[PDB]
Amino acid sequence: MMRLANGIVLDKDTTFGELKFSALRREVRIQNEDGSVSDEIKERTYDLKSKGQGRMIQVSIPASVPLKEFDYNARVELINPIADTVATATYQGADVDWYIKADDIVLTLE
């Protein structure tokens, strides 16, 4: 005898809006001093669509975080998402969309 919550107590705006999967843009890897890049990963950049200004957002998570094999338009939410200015600080002209570095990628539990 005990009552289990069938839903959520409160709502949080961490979900951004509707975050739905599109593809895996690119997994950037550890570059060797000699020049050539290694087979080991550094960060993983994903393609996610969000409701708002109509921009496809580039979500990058560190190598310590495993890959998530999600289906197309699967609803996800980010633990600690931050929109950076470090990418556009080293790149110029290639930055057609904006970058968001995240902690971990999970499914929308709310």
Image (spheres, rainbow, N blue to C red):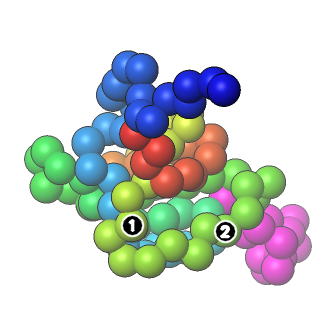
Give the amino acid type for the residue marked by disc 1 in the picture.
Answer: Ala
- Compared across the picture, whether 30 is left or right of 6 comes to right
Quarter assignment of residue 60: bottom right
Quadrant where the N terminus is found in the figure: top right
The residue nearer to you, when weighing 35 against 59, is 59
Q: Is residue 92 visible?
A: no
Q: Which residue is mark 1?
A: 74
Give the amino acid type for the residue marked by disc 2 in the picture.
Answer: Leu
Above or below residue 68? Residue 104 is above
Give the residue drawn at x 28%, y 60%. 49
The magenta segment is 29-43
- Compared across the picture, whether 108 is left or right of 13 comes to right
Pair 1/2: label in front? 1
**What is the C-alpha distance between the residues marked 1 and 2?**
14 Å
Tell me the element at label 1.
Answer: loop
Q: Which residue is mark 2?
A: 67
State the residue lying farthest toward the top. 10
Give the residue drawn at x 17%, y 50%. 51
Query: 10 Å neighbourhood of mark 1: few (<14), some, or many (≥20)?
Result: some
The residue nearer to you, when weighing 35 against 27, is 27
Query: 10 Å neighbourhood of mark 2: few (<14), some, or many (≥20)?
Result: few
Measuring from the top left, give residue 35's x and y in whole percent. 79, 74
Give the residue drawn at x 73%, y 55%. 65
- Compared across the picture, whether 49 is left or right of 4 comes to left
Give the residue drawn at x 67%, y 59%. 43
Pointers 1 and 2 in contact (C-beta within 8 Å):
no
Tell me the element at label 2.
Answer: loop
Measuring from the top left, give residue 37's x and y in whole percent. 77, 76
Q: Is residue 103 visible?
A: yes
Measuring from the top left, give residue 91's x and y in whole percent. 45, 54
Q: Would residue 104 be counted in the magenta stretch?
A: no
Quarter assignment of residue 103: top right
